[PDB]
Image (cartoon, rainbow over all chains, first blue to last red; front, side):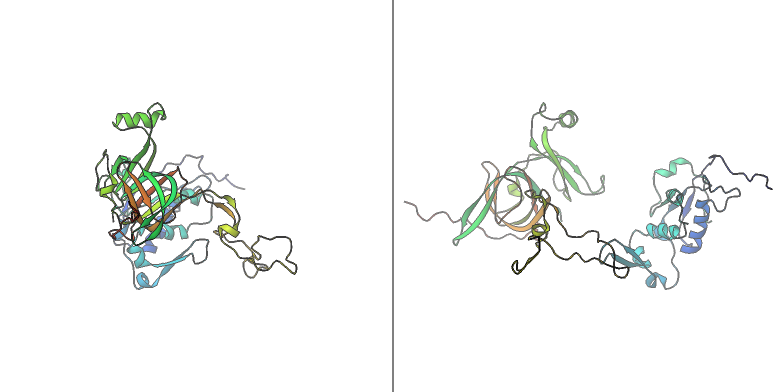
Length: 144
Length: 229
């Protein structure tokens, strides 16, 4: 029948990365970031335990936005109350803490799993560049 | 703007006769001249604030960690400590008279814990209305009637979060603003405040500067009795 298809035995090793968002578009970078963090790009992806990796984003405020969706695309957040719809533009998020928008964009492609909660906790979206994570000696790579 | 406040204990309710024969209700609060426990600057702490320590007690009468910190900080053991946001114009470890902060006719706001009604009905908590009781009105007499929130899979078939129903009323910290300052007593550092103010007579009440009327002062004088022999 089979060679008894194998996986890992909770032998996961994860590395830290440094990426700066200054000229890359939202979606086409977010898809690859999600692929990296979920373990999609790995050769021996083991969904049973994990095959993902960590993520740090530096200077998300300088990320580029495309076309008219800056002033045209609007995102809604609903609190469970009457009139809880908060409908804000992409440029509105630029005038605000924009890293959460990228966080939500990445989460939107996350499959409905009991591990996506821990796949997304390894993503640290920062508007700044200086933080305590720089002392962990990340495996520096970017532009995925 | 920068918020200036002072803490005190209410001791009773009375009234006074202001100028031009106006009977003004008086809340009497002995304000304690406090000594700030710390100041959080806008640069080192990234936001303006000042933690005040008030209701002074004995070191033996205070629990070990905080009284030891007070002694190491060369401060006095006090019953309560509270931070006031947006206040760095003062220094750390001072004895301050609030007379220089609030004036005779300044408008302030008061944060106080209201008298606890506990678990009360929405008839009083949310002030519902009830009409005639004659001609047959069913069992209840203090009720709300309809709680229509969706029947059948069409409209809601649920109950709304954040609804206004019966529950905990009173025993909660609320702020009332834009009330006049009436009376000062520098002999014992006590204040007489116009209107009606929450807070039990004996509890802790904070009186801070109103941010709707920061520098709105008015001429206020007290009508001493004209009947003098």
